[PDB]
Amino acid sequence: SVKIFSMLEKFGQFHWFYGISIGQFLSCFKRVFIKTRVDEILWLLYQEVYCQFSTALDKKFKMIMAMTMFCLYKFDIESEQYKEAVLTMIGVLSESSDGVPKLTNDDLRYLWDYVTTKSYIS
Image (tube, rainbow, N blue to C red; front, side):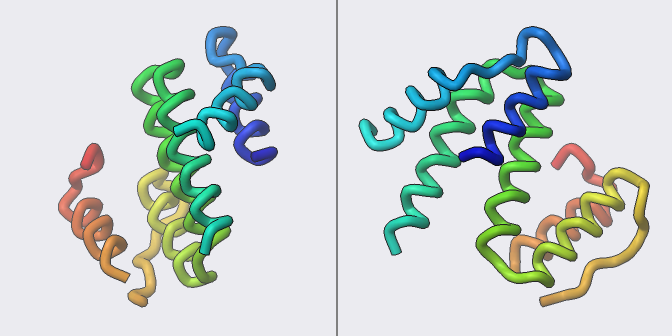
């Protein structure tokens, strides 16, 4: 929760409209319960906070938020090879680091097929 709030504070730092308040975040966390268990609360938290604070951002920041929240979840939950592969693929999207990823699950194969065929938007 504090990592997400720091992310949203950075979004509010970039533009005056994208600001975030602590009351809104706690209202969203209340709505999480209004609408392996701790991981289920964590997943519901991510889904609700994305569906709540995605509408306050434009297209580019929608993509930024979705990508970095998926990165946060998959990095904290899953293994190190997954993390390294995702950073290398985000880098080759960013054209700052160039290099093929190491094959392990299945979704990374689909992302690799999307990016090798130059389907950036996909």
